[PDB]
């Protein structure tokens, strides 16, 4: 069995972080998103993964995916292309897929969940896609805007965008499984699986929905990134080596208020308070009395004593001041440096900036 | 020789702090303002001080002035009255002053300076007031609005409020010395020495100005309070017992960036940074990594770890949160409690309040 992960795309919603690295390689918790998906696929038994590489063809994706040496898995890297939409990469990779009898997986690099992959053995009952349109129950389906009408027969009647009537609560989950015959349907041009191939499959009656019992989150947005991290860390606390604690004696003496993920190589202050559902990257340095409430600290980032970053994302090589407050949903770029006492209330800072002014309202720092 | 200190007044400009204690008893640095003035007068040799008490007749001024037991000085406390303006208390205290031959001092409880009181022996050269209208050079005389025209003869021509032309830079310093004959000029009614008696003396030619070489500040306003504290602390560091530090090993280990005043009974953190020109009151508790930049911490106030209060005044029995900012010119009342993470940018909080909302603009919390 083999999988195809759509690793292209410009990462527009995660823009301050995706101006440096592609969206699949943006670290979620303490690993890249695509790495979580590849680990799930390896747990399945999948050995071949095909990456649809359009954004950063060789500068980032090929070089940074040295994880092929680990994980006992190999990536094809034969879908280098110009932007071909969401469905075109499958048409391009038709040749490398060989049109074998065995079906193949399809995944997006923006989804996190328990990854129930027993949809391989299940849902083989005469489906063009064996429960391919995987769906999750979300009470906020109106703003998500992709509602899938799945009856008890699981035959997709239609796809509705922003439905006024309560047709259903299930929304697309971004995980698919296709028989290779679909390669005939996909044209060799720019197309979207969501808005071109899927309506045709639903009309033809070959599209079947698979329900998702566990948690699910599309983390392609900073708000969704934070909330999905909150949902995800409790699942992964016992999985990894990172009382009411996960890493309580890494550096000096500091307090942990709940689940978190602190890398072994990170030094965590003295008396700091690593809050619930917080991620600290490798080689990161945390000040004495910091408050890492719901923030993600990525790679070689340094945070000064007394800083309080909550529900915010800081970049890879930041140098945060001492007594700062980075609140709300604030995203910092690759090399942003913040002076002491600066308050950023949900402001997105582009890479390689220096912040020295208080920003009390959401905005963008060019 | 005796002095009279105008200790009445409602303290309107220092309102958040003067709703609990009178303006003379508001602690400046680590002592009441009137205590600084009385110490200066005792250094001169004045043994009798007459306090014109109108605001809080006996609830505050009489009880709290147990300093008469110390300092080797005695207060008459015979000018309890209804509001009689700035000049009326002298008419009321005419009798207790006994109309003796020896001149008498007059002071306001709002002025801080080096207190050059050699104007006693000096300026006796045929003056109704021996350099009574003491003046200080201020480059911002427009906003101060009380400009004294002092020529080389020192005869006050007139008083001008907000003068358009550059008549002069000297302004009233709030310290006067009077021959007792002035008791005949002051009528027994509500009057103002600044706007009724002093223009009359200037017209009569019996009003003489005394120049002030040293620093001076009227600290009746919170901004003026902070700036006068900044000017004053360096003079007082060597005077009192409170490298580049004044009190550097009081509690645990902490850093001092300049002049400060930390009471012996205050416990100061374990990594805190007591900044330049900061005052910490008695029995105060400071958190592990606080930052007291230019703030005055009064009495039994507790500050949590990571809090940064700069250029702000906290009340007597406050309980500040852990990771708060109290920035700009912010004044807190007697018993204000601030929750963790709250940011107060120059907001005045009335006594006995609880603050749990961020305030990014100057304002008043009722
Ligand atoms: N190979 C490839 N994959 C894409 C492309 N556009 C989107 N995807 C995939 O679709 C999923 C989500 O879309 P993103 O591009 O990341 O999000 P976006 O940048 O806001 O843009 P859209 O969702 O496409 O409107 C991710 O798996 C992407 O990798 C593309 O042009 N080429
Ligand atoms: N005894 C007495 N002293 C006063 C009175 N009003 C002002 N003073 C003195 O004048 C000086 C400054 O005035 P304050 O009253 O403190 O300041 P304020 O509250 O803004 O009001 P102003 O009188 O307009 O200045 C202080 O020494 C006061 O003690 C009063 O009604 N009675
Ligand atoms: Mg997405
Ligand atoms: Mg004053």
Image: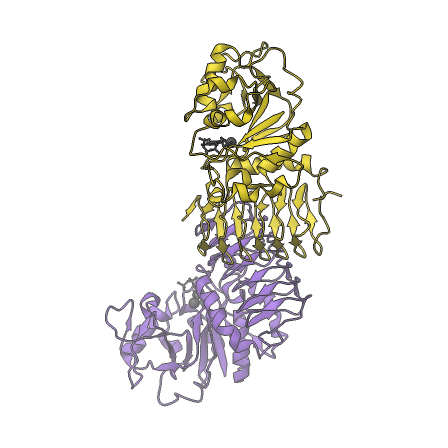
Chain colours: A purple, B yellow
Q: Is residue B111 visible?
A: no
Residue A226: percent from the left, percent from the top?
48, 65
Residue at horizontal 48%, vertical 17%? B184
Q: Is residue A212 visible?
A: yes
Residue A235: percent from the left, percent from the top?
52, 77
Q: Is residue A318 left or right of residue B192?
A: right
Q: Would you place residue B149 above or below residue A354 in this image?
A: above
The part of the image, by quadrant, that contains residue B34 is: top right
In terms of depth relative to the viewer, which is nearer, A142 or B230? B230
Q: Quadrant of ligand 1?
A: bottom left
Residue at horizontal 62%, vertical 44%? B279
The part of the image, by quadrant, that contains residue B174 is: top right
In terms of depth relative to the viewer, which is nearer, A33 or A70? A33
Residue B346: percent from the left, percent from the top?
48, 44
Q: Would you place residue A300 above or below residue B38 in this image?
A: below
Q: Residue furthest left?
A: A165
Residue B237: percent from the left, percent from the top?
70, 39
Residue at horizontal 48%, vertical 75%? A4
Q: Would you place residue B21 above or below residue A292 in this image?
A: above
């Amino acid at each position: 069995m083999r999988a195809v992960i759509l690793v292209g795309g410009f990462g527009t919603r995660l823009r301050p972080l995706t101006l440096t690295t592609p969206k699949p390689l943006v670290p979620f918790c303490n690993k890249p998103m695509i790495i979580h998906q590849i680990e799930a696929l390896k747990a399945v038994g999948v050995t071949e993964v095909i990456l649809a590489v359009a954004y950063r063809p060789e500068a980032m994706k090929e070089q940074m995916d040295e994880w092929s040496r680990k994980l006992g898995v190999s990536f094809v890297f034969s879908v280098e292309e110009e932007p071909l939409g969401t469905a075109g990469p499958l048409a391009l990779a038709r040749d490398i897929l060989m049109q074998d009898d065995k079906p193949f997986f399809v995944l997006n690099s923006d989804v996190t969940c328990t990854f129930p992959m027993q949809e391989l053995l299940d849902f083989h009952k005469a489906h063009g896609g064996e429960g391919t349109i995987m769906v999750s129950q979300v009470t906020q389906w109106e703003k998500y805007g992709v509602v899938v009408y799945s009856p008890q027969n699981y035959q997709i009647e239609r796809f509705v965008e922003k439905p006024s009537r309560f047709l259903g609560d299930r929304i697309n989950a971004g995980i698919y499984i296709f028989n290779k015959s679909i390669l005939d349907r996909i044209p060799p041009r720019r197309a979207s699986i969501e808005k071109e191939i899927f309506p045709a499959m639903a009309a033809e009656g070959q599209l079947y929905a698979f329900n998702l019992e566990g948690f699910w989150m599309d983390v392609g947005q900073p708000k969704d990134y934070i909330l999905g991290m909150t949902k995800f860390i409790p699942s992964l606390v016992h999985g990894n080596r990172e009382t009411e604690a996960v890493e309580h004696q890494r550096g000096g003496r500091f307090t942990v208020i709940g689940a978190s993920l602190i890398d072994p190589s990170a030094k965590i202050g003295d008396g700091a308070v690593i809050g619930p559902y917080a991620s600290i990257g490798a080689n990161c340095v945390i000040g004495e009395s910091c408050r890492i409430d719901n923030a993600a600290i990525l790679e070689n980032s340094k945070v000064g004593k007394g800083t309080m970053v909550s529900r915010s994302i800081v970049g890879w090589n930041n140098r945060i001041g001492s007594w700062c407050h980075i609140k709300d949903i604030s995203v910092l770029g690759d090399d942003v440096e913040v002076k002491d006492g600066v308050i950023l209330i949900g402001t997105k800072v582009l890479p390689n900036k220096d912040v020295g002014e208080h920003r009390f309202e959401p905005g963008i720092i060019m």
